[PDB]
Image 1 (spheres, rainbow, N blue to C red):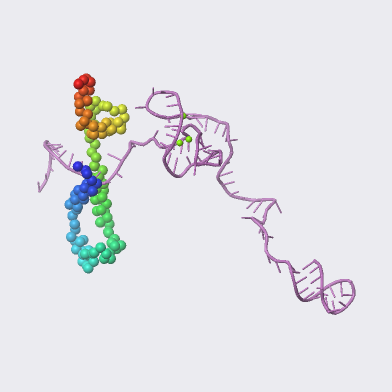
Image 2: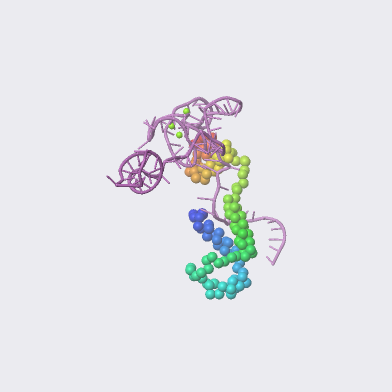
Amino acid sequence: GFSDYAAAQLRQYHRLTKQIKPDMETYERLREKHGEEFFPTSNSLLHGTHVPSTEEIDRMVIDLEKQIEKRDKYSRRRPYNDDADIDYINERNAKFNKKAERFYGKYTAEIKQNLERGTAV
RNA sequence: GUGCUCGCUUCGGCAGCACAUAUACUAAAAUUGGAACGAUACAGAGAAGAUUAGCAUGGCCCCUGCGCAAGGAUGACACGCAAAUUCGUGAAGCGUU
Ligand SMILES: [Mg+2]
Ligand SMILES: [Mg+2]
Ligand SMILES: [Mg+2]
């Protein structure tokens, strides 16, 4: 179940962070260029220095577009059958009756049987 | 401007001294814009059938009123394809390591 906005974030982060692959060439290049400060503390100096080249920002933009697509596929539309006896006259009435069947559907299980058998019992 | 000068010294002038010491949104204007109902056509008053009392609520909406009264159509407006972070099952067919 859902239970939190942070647990779905954590699941989504584990997915993205397992999908990524690091490049050791760029890593060792920047390590050899930066030297002493490549293992920084909270307070070293480099906060206002990095300028990423075009390939890095292109990779970030493509990854973020894929992430936006994965987010937009979150609520899949359930298929609409017209064989069920419809009990709504609007477009919002159908979804409100669906919410009523979600919440009160466990309790109001005898009266629907009474209705379908002819208002008896 | 006025007065006093044992001022020249006449009643003409001049000299000295004293008192008196800074108005005006500066126009009888040139300009510059936003504005008077109200007439012109249109336009028609909320609450799930119809006929209807209303009291609110919110603010780059005001009017009448001295009003922290009360009115203005319940003063008007508000009416919205009301979507905010973040997904997974199972088999089935096809291609692939
Ligand atoms: Mg009123
Ligand atoms: Mg009325
Ligand atoms: Mg009102």
